[PDB]
Image (cartoon, coloured by chain):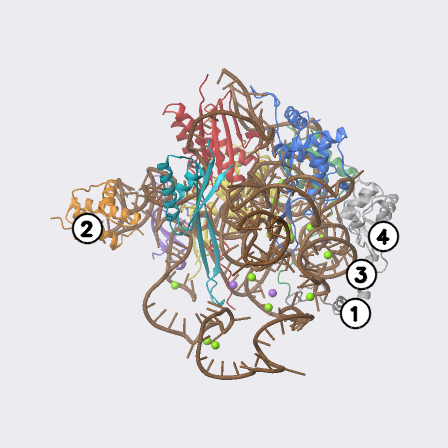
Chain colours: A red, B cyan, C orange, D green, E yellow, G purple, H blue, I brown
RNA sequence: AUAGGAUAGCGCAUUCGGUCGAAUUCUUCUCUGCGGGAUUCCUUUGUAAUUGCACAAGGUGAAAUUUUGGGCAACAGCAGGUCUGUGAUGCUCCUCAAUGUUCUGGGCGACACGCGCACUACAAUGUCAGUGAGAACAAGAAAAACGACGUCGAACCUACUUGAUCAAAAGAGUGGGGAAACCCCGGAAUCACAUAGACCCACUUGGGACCGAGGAUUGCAAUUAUUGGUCGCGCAACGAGGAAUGUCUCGUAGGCGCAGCUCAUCAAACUGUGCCGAUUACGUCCCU
């Protein structure tokens, strides 16, 4: 009876929340909401999600089953949340089942390329105030 | 195991609803009944926005009046007589406690 | 700006005067002392008091401070 | 007056909507010699509509007289076959 | 197993360098896969200079109410534009874009009291070059059969060559001529 | 469609006393005829068995006759009554599809009938005013 | 054509509306050049800062101090 | 080469291939088999009142049936209203601001009925529609064919 | 593949919210009443200091300066607005063919014209026809009435089915929800699509104003179109707008929809909500 090697992480961007379950399997298999990476559209968002792999290399992702479930937000925010969950999932798995020279060299590579791969973006929608059509845009003034 | 009784505690006052929930939990622990856990249901905000002026002159300023509603539930497997004994105490004003039997 | 109001400055001076021996150059330990030795509603005010209290301690080690009377 | 903008005018285009023998032969002969091939360019050279220009460019691509470089639902970019 | 990024997995960033001695610290040649980063580049005064130059081009394409906020569309237009630039120049489109940005803005302008000739900061040169090239391409494709990526490619290539057929170069020559007359 | 231009191509096609551009696609050239919209033209092409991808300049005389026949009597070619612009005539109670100058003439008849009965809508038409209850104040301003 | 200069000091924003920055610029030339380590005062349009570089073209006119 | 199995990977299911490519292949199979029931009103109606013109693809009903089958596969128990939200669109209201409108449930009811007569969709217990075992088998086998690049 | 490029997988192959399975275990996501956390805290060959109060860059960090956005907000005033909010009010006017109060009908909408503020556009960074992935804030039914024999049960919102052996809008049947429970795994629109789709620079498949005919729906009543839906009308301007002029510095502007609110029926308004997401400056006292 082989032991179960599994971790669960989350990535956040705006309202979108992505939860990534990373487990040791027969071979690498990463899917977002049940969809393989190669079927994710557009290519721009697919490349953004694939950045979580190509920045450190697919060798560290080998034999890892990653399932990412994303809810809330939009297509861009969900992709950014998914890529953060994948990057954090790799770090957490190496933290739990490896040593500290790993999960640090990987962490430095992730942080050197993009801080938002691991640290969530705190930017949120500013509330609308009365007397304004939006957060800042005041009503049009006329003088005569 | 036995029948399940649901205690629904709702109040406009957060302090009052918390004190009633703690008192109910402490009394249940004294009676040694098996309680599930006090679940804090999402707080609901009643919002009413009105124009400040009573006549409609000047800058169109507004008032945002908010009323917050707090709700808790406690599940315990006790006979109706025991739940009545636990519930029978002096509660704060403005706090509503409801009794429901789960099926 | 981050100018400390007279409320923070007066409280910090009183704290240093009464509990000089228990304070040091570290904000976090100074803050922990201040939570116990002061009564206030505002956590933000207590944090500001601790910051200036540490500043007063640093100035005290270099020399005397006007308004600080250590017996 | 009432119309403040100048309202300039441009010479109208007379692009053909159906191929003819001369333009079709030109598309089959001189177009595969171009380094950059797009329906807008072919429309300019052959004085034809972009719709039939793109249809002709598609036919050359299937015949492998030209190769497709950049492809999208709205954008097709072609080039001449190497050598 | 970690390779360097290539824009759209096709164009290499190796050797990407601006010929101008100025603008070298204000044109970013950092490698990236796509011109889409959710970075807070406007937080500081000069942080926007570190943003990748192609992404800056993508942001410049997001003008008018019908174009505001369409960054995925801008990336697609840039991808087609780079392919057309490669076909036109037989050179790395990233290098062509860098050359166009380096040469697309006037070095001397006029301000102010009477009009007086003044130098242009390198940050403004990069900003204006992107702004004018995008403006020229957008206005050229307004009611023309030629598509926007084709118009953008022609503007960038002409700007890279320094040709007067570029909208940005034409404005740069006029501004410099007026600035020289205002010396 | 890569088909060469036929020798009989007409840039202007006569159909129901209307000049129809042969450069346009068949359904979008039929809509030039008054009484036929984009939806009706597509249905006319379907009932006539004409490929909508063809240009209108390649339509032969027989197909033009079939198109004119279908537009004249859509109900004969199994076009539903809810698809016609005049389903129950207020004067005759008959279902038909007006086309060409028939639409203008029947509009004149409708205006004449309302203005003869002195109905409110007829008075508004006679005075050249909005008839559908729209606020004419700060509107139109010729 | 144009001579490169390095901004070694920002003297301050000048003129009404504060859109022009007055700076001290050291001409960048090789050793032995007549303009080697020659510092001139210039007026700059656009956001500039210390250690920025300018293309001066003409290097004779000196901005009046303000 | 391209259709080579990546490694340790066998077969294919839905959600593992291109959604449009599967739908086109499924619609092509429906038309080629010629057993599905196509209502005559599909040649005269718009897919929804929110559209301004009729569908331009002559095989739009076969495409819609394939899309409905895949939607039922993804969301078992979905009804006509749920599918209407999926196939809705923004409507042009003239000089008035645009608004979203759900697709007409009529064509969706026809599509579900046609898929039912094919033995692929059955009324799910406690409301809604669901795929039969035949429908699940058909969808996954077609997904594998898409991956293998048969396409018909 | 019709012509089929680019894009990770190299002890155990993946998938199945209807498989309306069965056992376990748990709190990574979600809910929240109190707490924690950030303060100039740390470091400068820095600015200043020869004192202090502080400032600027970087560090630390989810967050680095009033953390962000709001609420509250002194003292003096205005003959500002409101007697069309109140059983808040002096003086004054009408008071039984009344300036009270009902009912009927009409008007508040009426157009040679001028002005404020919006909506839709002038198109290809597009319009149509498809396909895909996908938010958040929120709302939801009734009594000292009435029907059934002191308790439900119909008013409200919805899902599913049917209508359907043939348009939309309808009309029906059944079930659920007092609302983290049903709606709902909330399939919003911007958006995306290598969709081998149509259009190709034209007042044109741009733009839908004006108008005609059928039908349905709310209401006691739709004529002066209540409002949806269908087919016509598109030959109504409009191809980017003179002098002038408004708002705005970060998840902001702009775009994009959604909910609430007015509501029997009707949002181009407002109050909120989320989605896509920049350019520019981080300066000055020239204008106000
Ligand atoms: K209509
Ligand atoms: Mg859809
Ligand atoms: Mg529109
Ligand atoms: Mg519109
Ligand atoms: Mg709109
Ligand atoms: Mg007054
Ligand atoms: Mg009074
Ligand atoms: Mg009025
Ligand atoms: Mg678009
Ligand atoms: Mg239209
Ligand atoms: Mg009435
Ligand atoms: Mg009507
Ligand atoms: Mg038109
Ligand atoms: Mg209003
Ligand atoms: Mg001033
Ligand atoms: Na106003
Ligand atoms: Na164009
Ligand atoms: Na007006
Ligand atoms: Na940091």
Q: Is residue B78 above or below residue I226?
A: above
Q: Chain of mark 2?
A: C
Distance from label 2 to label 1 (Cα)?
96 Å
Splitting the image into 4 quarters, where does residue E110 fall?
A: bottom left
Q: Are marks 4 and 2 on the same chain?
A: no
Q: Which residue is mark 2?
A: C14
Q: Is residue E87 above or below residue E46?
A: above
Q: Mark 4 and mark 2 in contact? Answer it, CB < 8 Å.
A: no
Residue sitting at x 37%, y 36%: B31
Q: Nearer the viewer, mark 4 or mark 2?
A: 2
Q: Which residue is mark 1?
A: F118
- Precedes in sequence: disc 4 or disc 3: 4
Task: Give the total number of marks visible in the rendering.
Answer: 4
Q: Which residue is mark 3?
A: F107
- Element at label 1: loop
Q: Mark 2 and mark 1 in contact? Answer it, CB < 8 Å.
A: no
Label number found at residue F16: 4
Q: Are marks 1 and 4 on the same chain?
A: yes
């Amino acid at each position: 009876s082989y032991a179960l090697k599994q971790v669960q992480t989350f990535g956040k961007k705006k309202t979108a929340i992505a939860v990534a379950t990373v487990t040791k399997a027969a071979q690498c298999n990463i899917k977002v909401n049940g969809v393989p990476l190669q079927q994710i559209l557009p290519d721009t968002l697919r490349a953004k999600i694939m950045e979580a792999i190509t920045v450190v290399g697919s060798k560290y992702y080998s034999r890892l089953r990653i399932d990412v479930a994303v809810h809330g937000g939009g297509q861009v925010s969900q992709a950014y949340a998914a890529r953060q969950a994948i990057a954090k999932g790799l770090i957490a798995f190496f933290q739990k089942y490896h040593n500290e020279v790993e999960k640090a060299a990987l962490k430095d590579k992730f942080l050197a390329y993009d801080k938002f791969l691991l640290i969530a973006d705190p930017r949120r929608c500013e509330p609308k105030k009365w007397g304004r059509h939006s957060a800042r845009t005041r009503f049009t003034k006329s003088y005569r | 195991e036995g029948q399940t009784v649901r205690l629904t505690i709702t109040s406009r006052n957060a302090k009052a609803v918390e004190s009633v929930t703690s008192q109910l939990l402490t009394r249940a622990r004294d009676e040694k009944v098996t309680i599930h856990g006090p679940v804090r249901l999402p707080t609901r905000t009643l919002k009413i926005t009105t124009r400040k002026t009573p006549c409609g002159n000047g800058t169109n300023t507004w008032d945002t009046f908010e009323l917050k509603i707090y709700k808790r539930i406690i599940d315990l497997h006790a006979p109706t007589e025991q739940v009545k004994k636990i519930t029978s105490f002096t509660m704060e004003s403005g706090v509503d406690v409801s009794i429901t039997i789960l099926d | 700006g981050k100018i400390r109001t007279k409320t923070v400055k007066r409280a910090s001076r009183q704290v240093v005067e009464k509990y000089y021996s228990k304070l040091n150059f570290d904000f976090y330990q100074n803050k922990r002392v201040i939570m116990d030795v002061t009564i206030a509603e505002s956590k933000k005010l207590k944090n500001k008091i601790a910051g200036y209290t540490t500043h007063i301690m640093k100035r005290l080690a270099r020399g005397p401070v006007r308004g600080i009377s250590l017996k | 007056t009432k119309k403040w903008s100048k309202g300039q005018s441009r010479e109208a285009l007379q692009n053909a909507v159906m191929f003819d023998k001369e333009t079709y032969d030109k598309l089959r002969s001189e177009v595969p010699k171009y380094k950059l091939i797009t329906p807008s360019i072919i429309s300019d050279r052959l004085k034809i509509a972009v719709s039939i220009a793109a249809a002709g460019l598609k036919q050359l691509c299937r015949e492998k007289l030209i190769r497709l470089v950049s492809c999208s639902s709205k954008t097709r970019v072609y080039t001449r076959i190497v050598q | 197993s970690s390779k360097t990024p290539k824009l759209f997995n096709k164009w290499s960033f190796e050797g990407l360098e601006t010929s101008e001695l100025a603008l070298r610290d204000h044109i970013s040649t950092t490698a990236a896969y796509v011109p889409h980063t959710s970075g807070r580049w406007q937080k500081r005064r000069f942080y926007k200079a570190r943003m990748p130059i192609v992404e800056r081009l993508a942001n410049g394409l997001m003008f008018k109410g019908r174009g505001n906020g369409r960054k995925l569309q801008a990336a697609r237009l840039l991808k087609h534009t780079l392919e057309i630039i490669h076909l036109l120049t037989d050179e790395n489109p990233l290098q062509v874009v860098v050359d166009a940005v380096s040469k697309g803005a006037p070095r001397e302008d006029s301000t102010r009291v009477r009009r007086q000739a003044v130098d242009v900061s390198p940050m403004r040169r990069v900003n204006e070059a992107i702004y004018q090239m995008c403006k020229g391409a957008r206005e050229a494709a307004f009611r023309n059969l030629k598509s926007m990526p084709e118009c953008l490619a022609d503007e960038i290539v002409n700007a890279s060559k320094g040709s007067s057929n570029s909208y940005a170069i034409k404005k740069k020559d006029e501004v410099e001529r007026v600035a020289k007359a205002n010396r | 469609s890569l088909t060469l231009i036929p020798d009989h191509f007409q840039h202007i096609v006569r159909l129901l006393n209307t000049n129809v551009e042969g450069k346009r696609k068949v359904p979008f050239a039929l809509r030039m005829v008054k009484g036929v919209g984009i939806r009706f033209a597509y249905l006319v092409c379907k009932k006539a068995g004409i490929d909508v991808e063809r240009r209108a300049g390649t339509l032969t005389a027989e197909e033009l006759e079939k198109i004119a026949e279908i537009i004249a009597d859509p109900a004969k070619f199994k076009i539903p009554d809810w698809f016609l612009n005049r389903q129950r005539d207020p004067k005759t109670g008959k279902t038909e599809h007006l086309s060409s100058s028939m639409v203008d003439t029947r509009l004149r008849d409708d205006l004449e009938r309302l203005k003869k009965m002195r109905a409110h809508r007829g008075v508004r038409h006679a005075y050249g005013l909005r008839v559908r209850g729209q606020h004419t104040c700060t509107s139109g301003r010729h | 054509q144009a001579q490169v200069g390095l901004i070694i000091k920002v003297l301050g924003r000048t003129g009404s509306r504060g859109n022009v920055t007055q700076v001290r610029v050291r001409l960048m030339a090789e050793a032995g050049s007549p303009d080697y380590n020659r510092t001139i005062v210039r007026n700059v349009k656009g956001p500039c800062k210390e250690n920025d570089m300018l293309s001066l073209m003409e290097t004779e006119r000196e901005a009046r101090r303000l | 080469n391209k259709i080579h199995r990546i490694g340790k990977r066998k077969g294919a299911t839905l959600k593992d291939v291109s959604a449009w490519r599967w739908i086109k292949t499924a619609a092509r199979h429906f038309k080629q088999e010629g057993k599905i029931f196509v209502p005559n009103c599909t040649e005269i109606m718009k897919s929804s009142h929110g559209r301004e013109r009729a569908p331009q693809n002559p095989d739009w009903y076969y495409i819609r049936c394939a899309a409905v089958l895949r939607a039922i596969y993804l969301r078992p128990g979905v009804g006509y209203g749920g599918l209407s939200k999926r196939f809705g669109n923004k409507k042009n209201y003239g000089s008035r601001p645009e608004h979203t409108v759900t697709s007409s449930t009529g064509p969706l009811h026809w599509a579900c009925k046609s898929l039912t007569k094919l033995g692929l969709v059955e009324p799910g217990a406690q409301s809604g529609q669901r795929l039969t075992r035949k429908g699940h088998k058909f969808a996954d086998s077609l997904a594998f064919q898409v991956q293998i690049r048969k396409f018909g």
